[PDB]
Image 1 (cartoon, chains in turn purple, orange, yellow):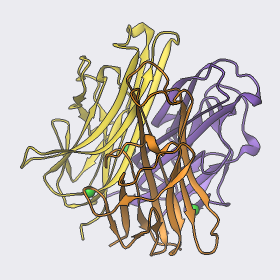
Image 2: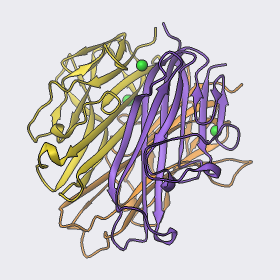
Image 3: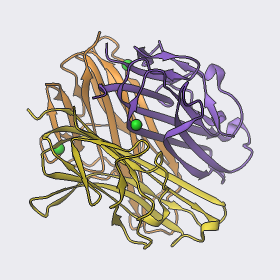
Image 4: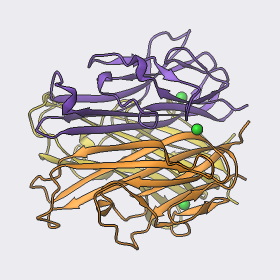
Length: 156
Length: 156
Length: 156
Ligand SMILES: [Cl-]
Ligand SMILES: [Cl-]
Ligand SMILES: [Cl-]
């Protein structure tokens, strides 16, 4: 039963704000959202089996003029895949991606997606979480905002 | 010992539109383009073996001012990795990515690439295709625009 | 003991010029950086065992007005994953990504990341390397700029 997970964002709990925050609302059993041998605790994917896993995340940001105004036109759309654990409580970034975007002008719709992927050694007990800026601009669709992991091979 | 695929764009045709369409011309036996156990049917990567596959797509877009007196003020460069089948035949997006761009500047060259990847459960018979907007802006090189998949493990 | 590598950028040595270059300084022995059954030489990841490998790279560019000014208003922020050989002086592009960005004044901070991935057939003696434009704008953090590979299955 090789470990893996593909979590999709749960808009039914999308926090407001523009500052860097951790996302804790994800789906694990519906649509493309699956999970196995791994446990999820409010946007905190816990590893139960040691191994080399490939981790990835796809976060889509969007804004339509019809939704109203945004604090500032110069945005910083960032995504951070973080690892946390009992021994190491502090957060450490495994991957970082994103871009500054000027969403000014009279344009009606603005969109931008970010993707990151990497190969990492994970020990049971360690947890991966997703931190992003401007969580209010996140796209709610499961094909738009998601993150996952899957074991590729055992640790030597 | 496991199926896989890496298809590269075949600009043999002349897709000159702006609306989102379904790319149907791909290579499977040239350069890096390859395939094993999987079958290609006019832009349709058909799965001939159940199991979990990692899907990925890289789409490059570019534009030159000389191709002028044509709107490239507001652009929506998007990519969609859709899945179809016999049952569950209605098109369902597995992954979405892209960005809005303003390529009306005095710059002689504009470029932007999109990348998406994810871990998915697939059953034999199901198909995977690629849909993008502004297909006439696609970069033809085999290293710029491509998509693919490879089985990571069997379904439990 | 499947072959793999996750290499992180070594800030120390990084071209301060404005030309596109091959990055030749990466870590393989600290932080998330790691390598197994592959050899890092002169910034090139040499394949020591024939097989199909998944290859990836994540490149982050950034700029703070305190660091001075950009070389030009409309920058080309690109990455090329290249394959060369220890036997013949051949050089081929496997993947390409990036985009043109206007980082002219205004904002106090500019950021942009690119990500590429792909399934490739590699043989012993072949080497994977990274070329980027605007190397002086590279983000030196290990979670920011890195590239890697891992064998998924043997050839044939
Ligand atoms: Cl799925
Ligand atoms: Cl290849
Ligand atoms: Cl690691």
